[PDB]
Image (cartoon, rainbow over all chains, first blue to last red; front, side):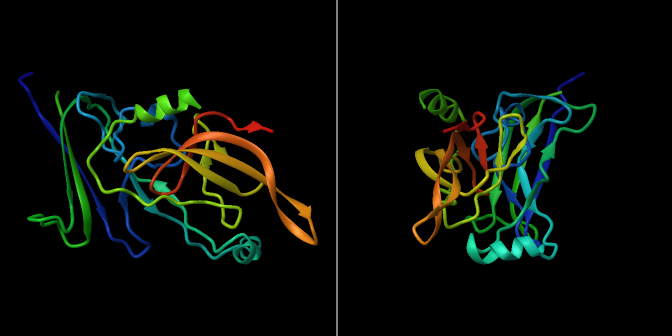
Length: 129
Length: 102
């Protein structure tokens, strides 16, 4: 078919549990899954993408259930505790894919930039099809 | 070490702010560590990091893995295994290989 250009979008927003963040630093992911991502976690121009592949890395805060008696014992000696994140990345939908042809990334507070209330950053990825 | 500099430097670059990395220590909780397969690696003690190269959002580190011991009239950490890894802006360690036990 005639060139049909898709537009994929993801927002990282402020949350009651703490900020979502666009990033490459995503847990429980094999090297191969991270292969085409730039250092910001945004997929590189000129890269073929297939259903399930990451376009934009994102992590959100999960969890915060009360600590175990074990995790409290440590909370004094080994240092104060710390928090768990989950993969909430933008991934190519079923039945789609192609070649990345452009990306756009905007950050709240940059000159001239106006994002939705709550949004810290937004990334768009364009793919051929 | 050199092949890990190679893998690290092949991460594509991007204009962004520099991140402040988590300098984990014998004093602090080690961050989550993953093998190249994506499997969680659970250390038997805390770690120390040595930065080798840096990228605005990722850095290359040598990770020293420790085991607490009886020393003096108290306890402190002494060495167990090491691995090269990249670390990101959530502080997570991505190992390039299973840790070499010393």
